[PDB]
Amino acid sequence: ARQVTIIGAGLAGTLVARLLARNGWQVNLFERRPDPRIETGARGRSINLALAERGAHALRLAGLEREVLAEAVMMRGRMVHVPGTPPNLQPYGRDDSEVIWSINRDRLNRILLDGAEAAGASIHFNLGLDSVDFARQRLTLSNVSGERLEKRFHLLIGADGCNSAVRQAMASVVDLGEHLETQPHGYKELQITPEASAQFNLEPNALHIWPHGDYMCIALPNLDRSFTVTLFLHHQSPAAQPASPSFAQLVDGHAARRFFQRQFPDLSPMLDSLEQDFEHHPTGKLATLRLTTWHVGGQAVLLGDAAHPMVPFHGQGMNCALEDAVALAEHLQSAADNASALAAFTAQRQPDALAIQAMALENYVEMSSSPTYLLERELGQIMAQRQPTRFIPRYSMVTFSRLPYAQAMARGQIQEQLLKFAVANHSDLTSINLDAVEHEVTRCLPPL
Ligand SMILES: Cc1cc2nc3c(=O)[nH]c(=O)nc-3n(C[C@H](O)[C@H](O)[C@H](O)COP(=O)(O)OP(=O)(O)OC[C@H]3O[C@@H](n4cnc5c(N)ncnc54)[C@H](O)[C@@H]3O)c2cc1C
Ligand SMILES: C[C@@H](Oc1cc2onc(CCC(=O)O)c2cc1Cl)c1ccccn1
C-alpha cells in the first residue's frame, strides 16, 4: 500500500485523507490543534461558511454530502440591506436546486474527521509541523510546549492552510516564485442571537449584506436562527482619505458601537454583544498569494489555502479547496508515480486557482456598492431566458456548476463585454435589438 503523510486536518486535508484511505493508501494526518470532537468545557464561537456546488460535489463523491447538508441552512439568495428601503431578496438561482448552504465550520470538521477515520486514516492531533528535511525524508513536529517528534515520510501533502508550514519548508529547497498581494480590509466577527434575529424578522434562508462602499457587513445563518455577522473594514485609513473609517479608528467596543449606530443603523440593534465581540474577537487578515510552484518533485505538494490563499468575497476558498482534494486524490491514485501525479495535479489546478483568485477580488464591488448596470442586468436576464445553455451569469457558473474556474471567467468576460457593448449609447431596452445581441450570444458562447 502507498503511504502518505498529510499536514493539516482542515477541509482539504481531511477530504483527501478519506479519498486516499478508502483507496487503500496508508494515511497519517497531523494536525496542530486539539481534536474538536473531544468535548471540553471551553466556550466556542460559531463561524459559518457558504458551501456551494463545487464543495458539495466533492463531499458527494466522498459519501459525506447528506450528513453535511442535514446540518446546513439553505441560502436562497442575497438579502441587501440599505436604510430606507425594505430588505431586497435577490435569488441566487432559477429555483431551490440553485442555492448555497450555510454550514457551521466545527460541525463540518467533525463530519470530515469522522469520515477520514471511517475510511482508515490515522489522525494525530496537537502536533504542528515545524520543519522538513527533504533530502533525509524526515520531518519535525511539535506540540504547543515545543516537545519535538521526528517522523520519516514518503509523500507529504501540505493541507495546512494559508500560513502553511509545508509551503515555508518547500520555499527552502525550491524557489516557489511567491507573489503576496495584501488586501486592505480586516474582518471582525459579531453575533446575532436567535431572539434578536426573530425580533427584527431577519430572513434565515438568505445571505445578508449591508453594503457601505469601502466597508460592509454580511451575515450567515445558523440552524438555531443565530447569525454570524462579519464586518469587512480597512485596517488603516489611507493617506488620501485620513478621515475614512478603519479598525485603527475603533479604539474599543464603545467606538465600534457608535460606528455601527451611525453607519449600520438597522443592524446595530440586532448586535447585543457588539462591544464584547469587538474587543474579544481578533481582527482577521485577508490576502491573495500566488505561487509559481506547488510541488517538490514527487515528495511534497500543496493544496487548498496552503497553495492559493484568496480573498473571501466569492465564498469559494473552501469550495476550491475541496475541489482540489478530489483532483489531488484522483491524480495520486491513477498516476505512473507520485512525481507525475503532482506535476499533473499542479498543471491542472493552477490556471483555475488563478481564475478564482481574480474573480474573488472582483466580487467585492458586486457586494459592497447603479444606473447603466441595471440595464445590463435586464439584458442579461433576457439573454439567459432565450439561451439558458449559453448565457449563464458568472456567479451561477462559479457557484452552481463545476465548469473549470478559468472557463467560467473566460465565458463571464465574453458575457460582460457583450452586455457592456450592447447597452452603450442606449437609454433603455426598447432601443436595443434583442435578436442581434442573441446572435452574438450564439456566435461567441458555445452551449454547455
Ligand atoms: C471565518 C471564515 C469564513 C469563511 N467562509 C467561507 C465561505 O463562506 N465559503 C468558502 O468557500 N470559504 C470560506 N472561507 C475560506 C475557507 O475556510 C478556506 O479557504 C478553507 O478552510 C481552506 O481549506 P484548507 O483545508 O486548505 O485549510 P484549513 O481549512 O484552514 O485547514 C488547515 C489546517 O491545517 C492546520 N495547520 C496549520 N498549520 C499547521 C502546522 N504547522 N502543522 C499542522 N497543522 C497545521 C490548521 O489548524 C487547520 O486544521 C472562510 C474562511 C474564514 C477564515
Ligand atoms: C463568510 C465569509 O465571507 C463570505 C462568504 C460568502 O459566500 N458567498 C459569498 C458571495 C455572496 C454574494 O455575492 O452575494 C460570500 C462572500 C463573503 Cl465575504 C468569510 C468571512 C470571513 C473570512 C472569510 N470568509
Image: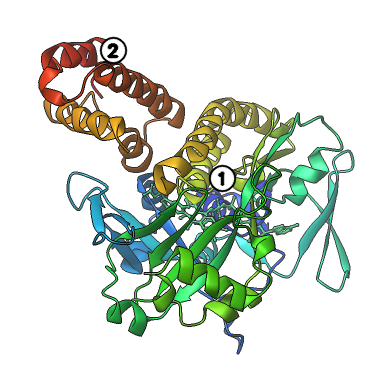
Residue visible at 31% across and 42% down? 400
Q: Looking at the picture, how far across and down is residue 413, in whole percent?
A: 39, 22
The quadrant of the rendering that contains the C terminus is top left
Q: Is residue 273 above or below residue 123?
A: below
Q: Residue furthest front?
A: 243
Seen from the viewer's position, the closer of residues 231 and 290 is: 231
Label 1: few (<14), some (14–19) or many (≥20) C-alpha neighbours in 10 Å: many
Q: CA distance from mark 2 to mark 1?
A: 30 Å
Q: Secondary structure at mark 2?
A: helix
Q: Which three-letter amino acid code belongs to the residue tagged 2? A: Cys
Label 2: few (<14), some (14–19) or many (≥20) C-alpha neighbours in 10 Å: some
Task: Kindly check if marks 2 and 1 are in contact, taking CB atoms under 8 A apart as contact.
Answer: no
Q: Is residue 387 above or below residue 56?
A: above
Q: Is residue 154 above or below residue 336?
A: below
Q: Is residue 190 above or below residue 382?
A: below
Q: Which residue is mark 1?
A: 311
- Figure quarter occupied by ligand 1: bottom right
Task: Determine the image quadrant of residue 208.
Answer: bottom left
Q: Residue furthest bottom?
A: 41
**Which comes sooner in the sequence, label 2 or label 1?**
1
Q: Looking at the picture, how far across and down is residue 361, in whole percent?
A: 52, 39
Residue 321 seen in render: yes
Residue visible at 33% across and 58% down? 82
Residue 249 vs residue 311: left or right?
right
> Which label number is shown at residue 444?
2
Q: Which three-letter amino acid code belongs to the residue tagged 1? A: Val
Q: Secondary structure at mark 1?
A: loop
Residue visible at 23% across and 50% down? 91
Residue 398 vs residue 307: left or right?
left
Residue 111 seen in render: no
> Which label number is shown at residue 59?
none
Task: Determine the image quadrant of residue 150.
Answer: bottom right
